[PDB]
Amino acid sequence: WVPPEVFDLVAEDKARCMSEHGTTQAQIDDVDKGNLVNEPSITCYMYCLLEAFSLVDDEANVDEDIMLGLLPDQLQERAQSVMGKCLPTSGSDNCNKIYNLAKCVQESAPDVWFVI
Amino acid sequence: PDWVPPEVFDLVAEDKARCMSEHGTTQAQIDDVDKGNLVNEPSITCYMYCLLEAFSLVDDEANVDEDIMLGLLPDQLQERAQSVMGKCLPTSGSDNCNKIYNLAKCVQESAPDVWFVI
Ligand SMILES: [Cl-]
Ligand SMILES: [Cl-]
Ligand SMILES: [Cl-]
Ligand SMILES: [Cl-]
Ligand SMILES: [Cl-]
Ligand SMILES: [Cl-]
Ligand SMILES: [Cl-]
């Protein structure tokens, strides 16, 4: 009569991206509180996490409709204004593109930090 | 220029709070849903709809995005998910929220041991 096994989607996706890039819990805690650094082990994790959610493609191009789709109706205009300052992405590789995007988001709206 | 601690906002926590509030959903109901026990009541089913839409898993016309959904599921569960989504999509029901109820019941009948929480 058993209850199902309950899979925490987010924790699965985070887990899989960590083990792929050698990312430590410490590093993801740093990102979770707004501290960014341009180190592949953590920045490729950020690229990986976004990709898992279809927010980016295999080149770290942002899907704007899906990214705006993460946020409530009340924040759409602020997000679009940040997206007009930070997109299209750019950098040396997929990981660096996401570092530069995360840094561009932080300085454009420094008072809030949005995490998955 | 100079770094200041930002107010940190957990999107998933915020989504749950807004959907709860928008659909008159109690905490007890949310807990039932996270264990996989469902009722065909709007305060539950529209809450599920609201959570899914917040991740572009569905649109605002009860159309589900299979590619997005597959991207979130664990590697354990890819072959099974494609088989279950093959049987359960496209969605079907009397209204937006009921469509998601039928999809949830379809998933459960087809894979009784698997359930997902956001
Ligand atoms: Cl590194
Ligand atoms: Cl882009
Ligand atoms: Cl960028
Ligand atoms: Cl570039
Ligand atoms: Cl992030
Ligand atoms: Cl559908
Ligand atoms: Cl309808």
Image (cartoon, coloured by chain):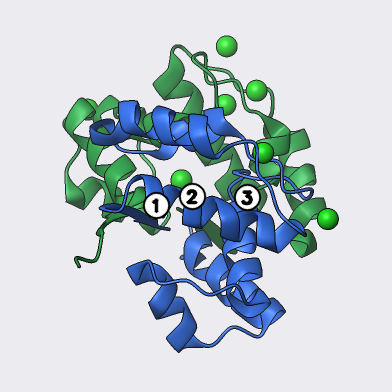
Chain colours: A green, B blue
Host chain of mark 3: A
Q: Is residue A22 left or right of residue B95?
A: left
Relative depth, front residue between B111 and B22: B111
Q: Is residue A29 left or right of residue B64?
A: left
Q: Nearer the viewer, mark 1 or mark 3?
A: 1
Q: Is residue A19 above or below residue A7?
A: above
Q: Which residue is mark 2?
A: B106
Looking at the rendered structure, the secondary structure element under dot 3 is loop
Q: Amino acid at mark 1?
A: Glu
- Looking at the rendered structure, whether the residues under marks 1 and 3 are on a common chain is answered as no
Q: Which residue is mark 3?
A: A70
Looking at the rendered structure, the secondary structure element under dot 1 is helix
On the image, the x and y values in percent for residue B55 come to 58, 48
Q: Nearer the viewer, mark 3 or mark 2?
A: 2
Disc 1 crowd, CA 10 A, few/some/many (<14, 14-19, 20+): few
Which corner quadrant holds the C terminus of chain B?
A: bottom left
Q: Are marks 2 and 1 in contact (CB under 8 Å)?
A: yes
Q: Amino acid at mark 3?
A: Leu
On the image, the x and y values in percent for residue B46 come to 66, 68
Relative depth, front residue between A76 and A39: A76
Q: Which residue is mark 1?
A: B109
- Looking at the rendered structure, whether the residues under marks 2 and 1 are on a common chain is answered as yes
Residue sitting at 67 percent across and 33 percent down?
Answer: A86
